Amino acid sequence: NAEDVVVTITETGYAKRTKTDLYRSQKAGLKQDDIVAHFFVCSTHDLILFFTTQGRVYRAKAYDLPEASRTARGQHVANLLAFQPEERIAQVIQIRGYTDAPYLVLATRNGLVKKSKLTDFDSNRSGGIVAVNLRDNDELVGAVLCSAGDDLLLVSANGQSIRFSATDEALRPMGRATSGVQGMRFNIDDRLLSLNVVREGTYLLVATSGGYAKRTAIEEYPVQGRGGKGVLTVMYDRRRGRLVGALIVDDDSELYAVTSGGGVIRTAARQVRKAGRQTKGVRLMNLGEGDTLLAIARNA
Ligand SMILES: [Ca+2]
């Protein structure tokens, strides 16, 4: 019954598993409908944690996802997990068990953060468990596994960034039902775009709605105290637009740039100009004149 599988969840919200041998076996212009938001290799009997925008976490075994192969869509996650109305996926984390890392750290749209012991989430309660108490106009945006020795990076849509060390002193572990503490401070005009764990030798790739992208080595993000305004990670220009993509990449990463007009461009991280934190980005190759960028996705 226990098999190795590839789990795929589309950006459109459909989930399936595929036996790894069949997946490999099943190896045209790219279509937005086929963009995969979450992809990993695991056991049928591993757990998948679905963190929602409303700050809940629903768990499922990988075998709870339907078998379908590479062409078929699978089941929509909101039906499979019985999400509340309007509830959407914010992040998905696959685990072998609740000791995979010491902590889960969550980050909210309005810049709040919280560390909780991962074992606090080991509950068979159905219908979703609260992972963070949100104010009425907040949403959960990020969730990562980490240890007290890690640094975290928060990036906002307007291009602020803050890096701080997730020590016990900086971020005391809190219960699931509690509210977050301030992670980055910004006004109503800004909102958090991404949360990531700092890893040596990687880059933060940012991209604006106007199609301008760059990647900056992670070592150029300065460590600061939690809760500040942070530092800029883009040279802002009215015409170039706000950020649409905040993500960590390495030299070998492959990405999909989702454009206006229903388009998708294959963009390797090696095509994206390595530059400084506040150096202007470079227009993505194969972006048509007048076309804009909606998102940056990963390619397996
Ligand atoms: Ca294309």
Image (cartoon, rainbow, N blue to C red):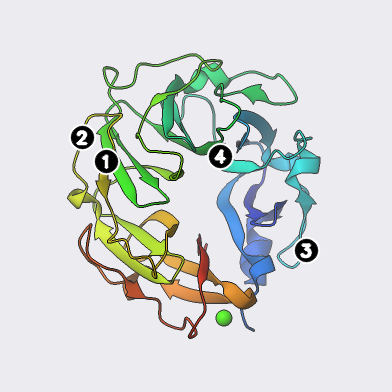
Residue located 69% across and 67% down the image: 33
Q: Amino acid at mark 4?
A: Gln
Q: Image check: 199 left or right of 129? A: left
Q: Say the numbered circle drawn on residue 230.
A: 1
Residue located 56% across and 51% down the image: 40
How far apart are labels 1 and 4 at the CA level?
Answer: 30 Å
Q: Provide the residue designation for mark 2.
A: 224
First along the sequence among labels 3 and 2: 3
Q: Provide the residue designation for mark 4.
A: 94
Q: Provide the residue designation for mark 3.
A: 72
Residue in front for this viewpoint, 112 or 6: 112
| Dot 4 crowding, Cα within 10 Å, few <14, some 14–19, many 20+ | many
Looking at the image, is 91 positioned above or below residue 297? above
Residue 149 image-quadrant placement: top left
| Dot 3 crowding, Cα within 10 Å, few <14, some 14–19, many 20+ | few
First along the sequence among labels 4 and 3: 3
How far apart are labels 1 and 2 at the CA level?
Answer: 8 Å
